[PDB]
Image 1 (spheres, rainbow over the protein chains, first blue to last red):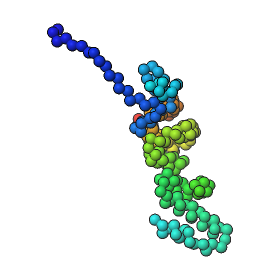
Image 2 (image 1 turned 180 degrees about the vertical axis):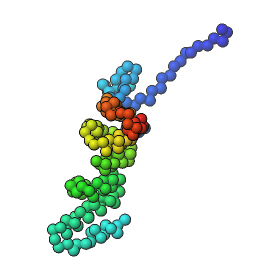
Image 3 (image 1 turned 30 degrees about the vertical axis):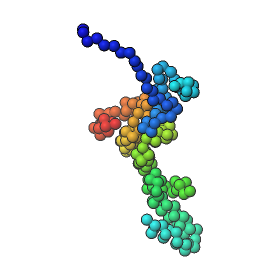
Image 4 (image 1 turned 120 degrees about the vertical axis):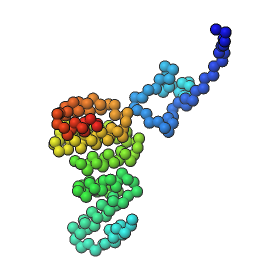
Length: 49
Length: 59
Length: 88
Protein backbone atom coordinates (compact mmCIF):
# COMPACT_ATOMS: atom_id res chain seq x y z
CA UNK A 1 0.00 0.00 0.00
CA UNK A 2 2.34 2.68 -1.33
CA UNK A 3 -0.09 5.61 -1.65
CA UNK A 4 -0.24 6.61 2.00
CA UNK A 5 -2.15 9.76 2.96
CA UNK A 6 -3.34 11.60 6.06
CA UNK A 7 -5.93 14.14 7.22
CA UNK A 8 -4.74 17.01 9.40
CA UNK A 9 -7.45 19.68 9.58
CA UNK A 10 -11.20 19.88 10.17
CA UNK A 11 -13.63 22.77 9.63
CA UNK A 12 -17.06 22.66 11.29
CA UNK A 13 -19.58 25.04 9.69
CA UNK A 14 -22.89 25.23 11.58
CA UNK A 15 -25.89 27.16 10.24
CA UNK A 16 -28.07 26.54 13.29
CA UNK A 17 -29.58 29.96 14.12
CA UNK A 18 -31.58 28.72 17.09
CA UNK A 19 -35.07 30.02 17.80
CA UNK A 20 -36.38 30.75 14.28
CA UNK A 21 -37.68 28.31 11.65
CA UNK A 22 -37.03 28.97 7.94
CA UNK A 23 -40.05 29.60 5.69
CA UNK A 24 -39.92 26.18 4.01
CA UNK A 25 -40.81 24.10 7.08
CA UNK A 26 -43.93 23.60 9.18
CA UNK A 27 -43.22 21.47 12.25
CA UNK A 28 -45.34 19.14 14.35
CA UNK A 29 -46.06 19.84 18.02
CA UNK A 30 -43.65 17.36 19.71
CA UNK A 31 -41.17 17.39 16.82
CA UNK A 32 -37.57 16.16 16.86
CA UNK A 33 -35.23 18.67 18.49
CA UNK A 34 -32.05 17.06 19.86
CA UNK A 35 -28.80 18.29 18.30
CA UNK A 36 -25.60 16.47 19.28
CA UNK A 37 -27.66 15.12 22.20
CA UNK A 38 -28.53 18.62 23.50
CA UNK A 39 -31.95 20.26 23.63
CA UNK A 40 -31.45 23.81 22.24
CA UNK A 41 -34.67 25.16 23.81
CA UNK A 42 -33.70 24.62 27.47
CA UNK A 43 -31.14 27.46 27.47
CA UNK A 44 -30.30 30.71 25.72
CA UNK A 45 -29.35 30.87 22.04
CA UNK A 46 -25.67 31.72 22.51
CA UNK A 47 -25.02 29.12 25.21
CA UNK A 48 -26.77 26.41 23.18
CA UNK A 49 -24.85 27.37 20.00
CA UNK B 1 -69.82 42.86 -9.82
CA UNK B 2 -71.88 45.69 -8.32
CA UNK B 3 -75.13 45.65 -10.31
CA UNK B 4 -77.00 43.29 -8.00
CA UNK B 5 -75.38 45.09 -5.06
CA UNK B 6 -76.89 48.44 -6.05
CA UNK B 7 -80.35 46.91 -6.44
CA UNK B 8 -80.05 45.30 -3.01
CA UNK B 9 -79.03 48.71 -1.63
CA UNK B 10 -81.45 51.16 -3.21
CA UNK B 11 -84.76 49.34 -2.98
CA UNK B 12 -85.98 51.15 0.15
CA UNK B 13 -89.67 50.80 -0.75
CA UNK B 14 -90.54 48.37 2.05
CA UNK B 15 -93.74 49.08 3.98
CA UNK B 16 -94.06 46.08 6.30
CA UNK B 17 -92.19 43.93 8.80
CA UNK B 18 -91.78 41.10 6.28
CA UNK B 19 -90.69 43.52 3.54
CA UNK B 20 -87.85 44.93 5.64
CA UNK B 21 -86.91 41.41 6.78
CA UNK B 22 -86.70 40.44 3.10
CA UNK B 23 -84.50 43.48 2.50
CA UNK B 24 -82.20 42.30 5.31
CA UNK B 25 -82.05 38.73 3.99
CA UNK B 26 -81.31 39.85 0.43
CA UNK B 27 -78.59 42.23 1.63
CA UNK B 28 -76.93 39.56 3.77
CA UNK B 29 -76.95 36.72 1.22
CA UNK B 30 -75.66 39.01 -1.57
CA UNK B 31 -72.70 40.16 0.59
CA UNK B 32 -71.57 36.50 0.95
CA UNK B 33 -72.07 35.63 -2.77
CA UNK B 34 -69.42 38.24 -3.72
CA UNK B 35 -66.52 38.53 -1.21
CA UNK B 36 -62.78 38.87 -1.81
CA UNK B 37 -61.98 36.19 0.77
CA UNK B 38 -62.78 32.72 -0.67
CA UNK B 39 -63.48 31.20 2.75
CA UNK B 40 -66.63 33.28 3.33
CA UNK B 41 -68.08 32.79 -0.18
CA UNK B 42 -68.03 29.00 0.25
CA UNK B 43 -70.70 29.33 2.96
CA UNK B 44 -73.28 31.00 0.66
CA UNK B 45 -74.90 27.73 -0.45
CA UNK B 46 -75.53 26.73 3.17
CA UNK B 47 -76.88 30.12 4.24
CA UNK B 48 -79.68 29.97 1.66
CA UNK B 49 -80.95 26.83 3.42
CA UNK B 50 -80.20 27.69 7.06
CA UNK B 51 -81.01 31.28 8.07
CA UNK B 52 -79.68 31.26 11.68
CA UNK B 53 -76.26 30.66 10.16
CA UNK B 54 -76.73 34.07 8.60
CA UNK B 55 -76.65 36.97 11.09
CA UNK B 56 -73.30 35.48 12.21
CA UNK B 57 -71.19 36.33 9.15
CA UNK B 58 -73.01 39.66 8.72
CA UNK B 59 -70.34 41.75 10.46
CA UNK C 1 -74.97 16.93 6.40
CA UNK C 2 -73.41 17.26 2.98
CA UNK C 3 -72.94 21.01 2.63
CA UNK C 4 -71.46 21.31 6.12
CA UNK C 5 -68.54 19.09 5.19
CA UNK C 6 -68.40 20.14 1.53
CA UNK C 7 -67.53 23.65 2.69
CA UNK C 8 -64.98 22.52 5.28
CA UNK C 9 -62.87 20.62 2.75
CA UNK C 10 -62.87 23.60 0.39
CA UNK C 11 -61.44 25.76 3.17
CA UNK C 12 -58.52 23.44 3.90
CA UNK C 13 -57.43 23.17 0.26
CA UNK C 14 -57.53 26.97 0.04
CA UNK C 15 -55.53 27.64 3.20
CA UNK C 16 -52.54 25.43 2.39
CA UNK C 17 -50.29 24.17 5.18
CA UNK C 18 -52.03 26.34 7.76
CA UNK C 19 -55.24 24.36 8.41
CA UNK C 20 -53.36 22.38 11.09
CA UNK C 21 -54.47 24.99 13.62
CA UNK C 22 -58.06 23.77 13.36
CA UNK C 23 -57.28 20.05 13.70
CA UNK C 24 -58.06 19.77 17.45
CA UNK C 25 -61.42 21.49 16.94
CA UNK C 26 -62.57 19.49 13.91
CA UNK C 27 -61.21 15.97 14.31
CA UNK C 28 -62.75 14.90 17.67
CA UNK C 29 -66.28 15.72 16.48
CA UNK C 30 -65.85 14.48 12.90
CA UNK C 31 -65.06 10.91 13.93
CA UNK C 32 -67.93 10.91 16.42
CA UNK C 33 -70.31 11.70 13.56
CA UNK C 34 -69.25 8.67 11.50
CA UNK C 35 -70.11 6.21 14.28
CA UNK C 36 -73.67 7.60 14.62
CA UNK C 37 -75.35 8.32 11.24
CA UNK C 38 -77.35 6.65 8.41
CA UNK C 39 -76.17 4.23 5.68
CA UNK C 40 -76.84 7.00 3.14
CA UNK C 41 -73.87 9.19 4.05
CA UNK C 42 -71.05 7.01 5.42
CA UNK C 43 -69.35 6.56 2.04
CA UNK C 44 -69.34 10.31 1.41
CA UNK C 45 -67.92 10.97 4.88
CA UNK C 46 -65.16 8.41 4.31
CA UNK C 47 -64.23 9.98 0.98
CA UNK C 48 -64.11 13.46 2.53
CA UNK C 49 -61.98 12.12 5.38
CA UNK C 50 -59.59 10.70 2.79
CA UNK C 51 -59.33 14.10 1.13
CA UNK C 52 -58.74 15.74 4.51
CA UNK C 53 -55.93 13.30 5.31
CA UNK C 54 -54.42 13.93 1.88
CA UNK C 55 -54.34 17.66 2.61
CA UNK C 56 -52.99 17.30 6.16
CA UNK C 57 -50.17 14.74 5.47
CA UNK C 58 -47.98 13.92 8.57
CA UNK C 59 -49.94 15.99 11.16
CA UNK C 60 -52.64 13.23 11.35
CA UNK C 61 -50.71 11.07 13.85
CA UNK C 62 -52.77 11.38 17.08
CA UNK C 63 -56.04 10.21 15.44
CA UNK C 64 -54.78 7.12 13.59
CA UNK C 65 -55.94 4.72 16.32
CA UNK C 66 -59.55 5.89 16.09
CA UNK C 67 -59.40 5.99 12.29
CA UNK C 68 -58.12 2.40 12.15
CA UNK C 69 -60.78 1.28 14.62
CA UNK C 70 -63.48 2.76 12.38
CA UNK C 71 -62.05 1.04 9.29
CA UNK C 72 -61.90 -2.25 11.20
CA UNK C 73 -65.52 -1.93 12.33
CA UNK C 74 -67.00 -0.95 8.95
CA UNK C 75 -65.13 -3.33 6.59
CA UNK C 76 -67.69 -5.79 5.18
CA UNK C 77 -67.97 -8.06 2.06
CA UNK C 78 -70.22 -5.37 0.46
CA UNK C 79 -68.62 -4.35 -2.83
CA UNK C 80 -69.37 -0.63 -2.60
CA UNK C 81 -67.66 0.42 0.64
CA UNK C 82 -64.60 -1.74 -0.07
CA UNK C 83 -63.29 0.41 -2.93
CA UNK C 84 -63.76 3.58 -0.88
CA UNK C 85 -61.86 2.09 2.06
CA UNK C 86 -59.09 0.84 -0.25
CA UNK C 87 -58.64 4.32 -1.72
CA UNK C 88 -58.58 5.71 1.82
